[PDB]
Amino acid sequence: SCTQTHWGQCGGIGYSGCKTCTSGTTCQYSNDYYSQCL
Image (tube, rainbow, N blue to C red; front, side, top):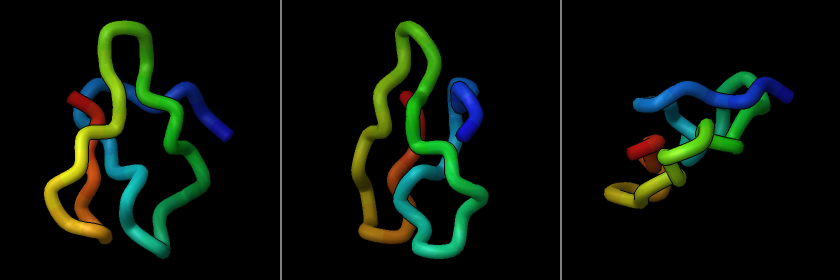
């Protein structure tokens, strides 16, 4: 699993593995399927 960039979908039950947002960013929730690195 990648070290996921700033602005990066962890949420989506479909996405290519990586949830771990890079230093400064954590995966901030909006929807279940749209949770994004911010």
